Image (cartoon, helix red, strand yellow):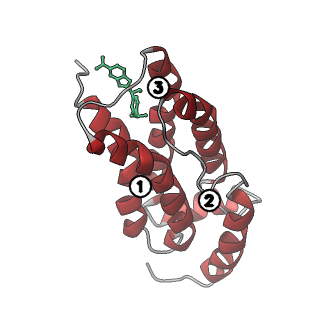
Amino acid sequence: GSPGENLKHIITLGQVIHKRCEEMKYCKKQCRRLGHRVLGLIKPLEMLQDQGKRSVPSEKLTTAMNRFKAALEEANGEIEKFSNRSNICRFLTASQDKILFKDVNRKLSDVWKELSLLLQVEQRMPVSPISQGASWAQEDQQDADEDRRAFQMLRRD
Ligand SMILES: CO[C@@H](c1ccc(C(C)C)cc1)c1nc2ccc(C(=O)O)cc2[nH]1
């Protein structure tokens, strides 16, 4: 079953990244951006329900959100795997880019901006406070740039 309690799970899924990012060590510097950004997504959605009783618009919106809830599985899941030491180099060397959750963060912004329009019309929540609007990938590359360099010189674990 998926009662009202689910509302707390969906929002928690995105929060899990915040703590998961702390677990990392090497690429932890890069993931830090993914966890800080993702937090701003379920931030308003979490506090919302906190305001009063079960806060949720029409069911039609549930469908759009269903796509976002899964978006977290991508980041969270990836973090669990990346947690390893060799796995990091595996992708790093098997990817011209430097960021680990590059493609992941990409969809994250889409799943958010996709439901945002529905959230702004459904609920009185001021979406896109300031952090949104511009792709967070641009800045993500900066961190990954230096993060990748340091990785070059990593013998021990
Ligand atoms: C995936 O969508 C979630 C959801 C999560 C967060 C939000 C914030 C407040 C915008 C809104 C909606 C959701 N929609 C629902 C509709 C009905 C019921 C019900 O009790 O029958 C439960 C629901 N859960």
Left or right: 11 in relation to 98: left
Q: Tell me if the residue at label 3 has its CB under 8 Å from ligand 1.
A: yes
Q: What residue is disc 1 on?
A: 17
Q: Which residue is mark 3?
A: 66
- Mark number displayed over residue 60: none
User: Mark 2 falls on what kind of element?
Assistant: loop
Give the image quadrant in which the ligand numbered 1 is located: top left
Query: What amino acid type should be assigned to the residue bearing mark 2?
Result: Ser
Residue in the picture at 49% in, 21% down: 61
Q: Is residue 99 above or below residue 67?
A: below
Front residue of 13/118: it is 118
Query: Visible in this render: residue 87?
Result: no
Where residue 130 sits: x, y (%)? 63, 59
Secondary element at image label 1: helix
Q: Position of residue 96 (x, y in %)?
A: 77, 59
Q: Give the residue at mark 2.
A: 131
Q: For the residues marked 1 and 3, what is the alpha-carbon distance in whole angstroms?
A: 18 Å
Residue pictured at 60% horizontal, 58% vertical = 100
Q: Amino acid at mark 1?
A: Ile
- Rounded to the nearest whole Å, what is the CA distance between mark 2 and mark 3? 23 Å
When asked about the image quadrant of residue 30, the answer is: bottom right
